[PDB]
Image 1: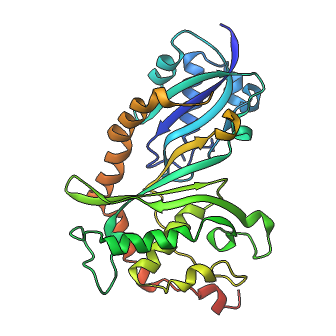
Image 2: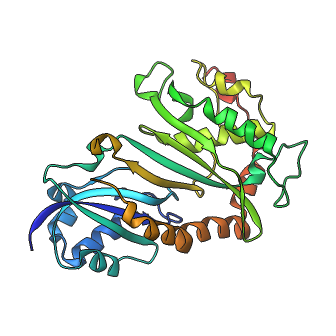
Length: 313
């Protein structure tokens, strides 16, 4: 078969996985097995992924899902390649699209941004004194407006050293650019109310989104004053609550800059279908049955936002 550089649009439910990147199970473990078994790549390209020029656009962490992950690599362009790769993957990892590209196209180098969604039960925004705290809570317009006012403060370029680990106040690598961040109107599925927070950033650091969400959750519920968000830009350390990984879903890898044609419009039905068969059921079912968010929320009352600073740390 002809040898070509391709770009793959893929999706996965990330629950129980330790991340995308091959490392304890990872998405790429399964993807590389499927690529070898389908005959897309020789075995030694599975052993040394550099040999097929492999790149992934988003390093999703432990438990994180994807509706629109993008990888690029060189393959033998076999017949019915998508069907064949998919036949060797579990149902909860799916290759949704393929594009042929110029041989030197490297997806991670060409993408300009990533958008993530964070799907959460709305009682994560319920004020600890003013609102009921369980599944019966319904999000008010006022509280949604407060969430959005707070999330908008993240937009721009900021030093996010307090939103990751092993980076100091003066570290320019801790500066990141957020293009958009907001929370949609809430909706009900399976009799429970959820909302989606969407964040588009040029790039993200370890723990960053989970802590960006965790802080706004903590403030909105009343565990910290709204002033702590501004304070977290400061030089001094703030200990920022980290929300669970379960609700975090990579939605899109952006190629608008490059396109100005990596457009996945034709795959929108496949994306929606996978979200409904695998991502939504896993996240909502896990919230309903195992109460992941509720349990994490129950740990906020003892979170000390100043613990590190108090130890002169």
